[PDB]
Image (cartoon, rainbow over all chains, first blue to last red; front, side, top):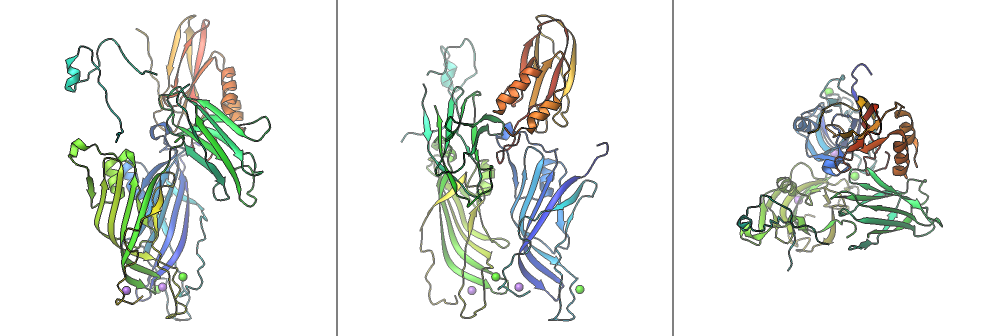
Length: 161
Length: 304
Length: 123
Ligand SMILES: [Ca+2]
Ligand SMILES: [Ca+2]
Ligand code: NA
Ligand code: NA
């Protein structure tokens, strides 16, 4: 191990509701769940201080927690985000080992000019939810895809798209 | 009633400073702790489903010099599980020794530090869950042996169903939220304020926990869309450790339990889910408070 | 009024670092204190006059899903002449050892074997 390697993050995503599509402005809106899990020995928690296995940071952005802790973390952004995102049950967990995890249910509005409505209603479309990191490949990279739940959740009656 | 909490005792022999509030330790030692011990024992029948197959229970607080015994037993012919005891950090202090006949996996320990804060573990890690119903009697003892979740009574009432988005499968509602819950660690001593009541107003249980740096039963409306307009927000705490939260609110919630297939002859479910934001092992909902009419009858109004 | 030295180091993988004491004397009393200053390290400090390698069978103790206090106690007592386990300061990561005979000794500074988690026991 003579060269310094990027620590490896396993990311996961799932969608619960396709809740809006703006066909004029070529964007849409979706509700889903975001998980990143990643092993970094550098915030190792020693247990006798807390008296626990788990240290929790709640209601803040990886970015904000990095700033508070003043160390590097795998921050990200939804790539085509329009305005603001409504994030609930936001949290980042860190165990003693240097194992860390991010969990966030969210409701985001995304620009998709991959829309073409030329053969409407016989058109077909791509909803792409791009999650980029905000740090280079040489620090963090996505290594695995976590199938933490059904990616798309089958309520079939619902039906519009 | 009797009252509870922690204290600082200053003892002085020929030292008038001690009655003046002034304790700086000096001179030759004259006093300390004055004297089987007291025992505490608990039952619990634990159950181990496919869902829950490792279980841990935080013990509460042994003095240096205290002995801890624990025993598991099968309810039916279910398998003998793995037993162990551990500190809060997870460093092991004991293991379960399966007994002479082979019916009870027992474990033993007596205590080292001026705080030993022990944690009991039982796992059904040994085999694939066949019908997921093997259940156990757990006996425990020192010489309220387990530290228990404090119990919150929650209540809700709706005054107006003020919006339904049929396209986006969500709705909006106006209502009233109350949580009442008795936690001694909250305790206000009266001579500071000069009152029975301490009030925190216009902030989220979360925010007040942060300010106070203690644990409280925070919550979230589960399917909340964006922000909620909360008015007459407040949390009350009396000296006793009795506490209450009151909040009129106006919230927008995602309900994809909508099906509009038999419109207008469809019928629907408006579900207002209130989850806690802390586990079962710290706070749980114990009662439902019917504090007012749950649904408020203005009938002329009429749309749904 | 006693004589004191400071050291700082890093335990990389669990495996420890050796510090040599030449010219130790019959009767002399060695005091050692090892405090965590970063990471999740639970310290283990020990003394031995002969270098036989702890990493291999401490490695073999890790392999056993087996109790363990007795298994580790037996191994430690056999490999070291005197030893102690970090446990913050509650386990008083520290020992006192009276030197039995003249010679060169070695103190071991490393990690113990402990469980860190409540969700599963995997030490
Ligand atoms: Ca386009
Ligand atoms: Ca539906
Ligand atoms: Na309406
Ligand atoms: Na829609």
